[PDB]
Every structure is written in C-alpha cells, then in structure tokens.
Figure (tube, rainbow, N blue to C red):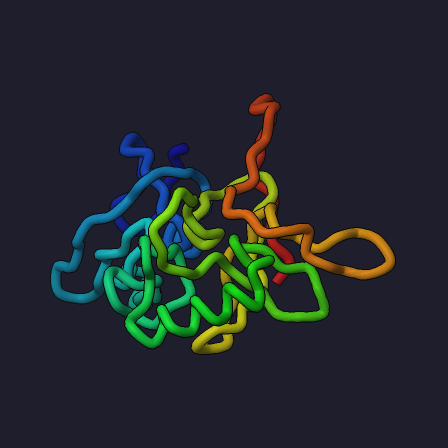
Length: 185
C-alpha cells in the first residue's frame, strides 16, 4: 500500500513496505523494500531481512541481520553466524513447534530460525502487515519485541500449546476490508 511517512518508502507512489523495518517505522503496506539512504544526519539502509538502520527523527531503527548479525527480525535465509546455526539446530529440534513467528503460551515470543537445505518459507519476522500479525516479546540473544503472525500459534483448549510445526505466513481470503489490525504489546 501507500502512506505518507518518514524516509523514502510508500510515500505517495512508490508503495514499498519493509518487513519488520516497515512495521516498525511505518505500518501501512506490504512489499520488498531495501536501499541505502543517509545524507549526513541519519541512516536508512534496512531490508526485508537484514541488519541496517532506518531514519526515524534522529532515531535509527535496529533491523535483523543482513548476513551475519545477532538480531531478532526479518531473517535472511540463515540469519545469524556459526554459533547461531548451532543454537538453531539444537533449538529447532527441541522447539520444532517454532517453525515460524508465533507465540501465545506462558512463554516468550518465538520465530522461525534455522539453516538447512530443504523446501521451506520465510520466518514470522519476515512477514508483512498480515491480518493476523501483531508483535510479542521474543526470547533470543536479547529480550525484545518482534512481529507475531498466525501459524504455530497455541491451542485454545485446556491450556495454551502450539498447534504444530510449519513455516507459513498467515493469509486471508476476503481482501474486501481494511486488514490492518493492531498489536497488544
């Protein structure tokens, strides 16, 4: 979509949103945005899944990892470094139910983080302003809040428990209304 906001994105024509960056700077669109921008005051070279900084009124934003940066945002293929890969192989095996950005249990927020050769999809932090995506406090290499989409959400029964394991961003089948709700945290 398009909406008047800071920086150069989805201003009034070039409708281009940014995964976590967009939802963190301007939530009013959904597309692949990424480009350097810094005159001599701020920095804006984020990406739908990288480690950069946006230009927010004398306030630079913190994105995920562009190649090898310890961040909890729009992952990029194998977001993270060596250690990260070792923590994902052991963390995913014990929390396979975290194959996406979801969270609704007595625990913190989780997101799809892993590196392997197979057919999969982007993590939750790499999702757009979906109709079922908010943002809860994730627990990784640093306490913080990240976008939370619908997928491995907990079960609404005798207790909150992730449904299963899968990496797929929540999608609707109406597109006949303003699908742009608000988070809780």
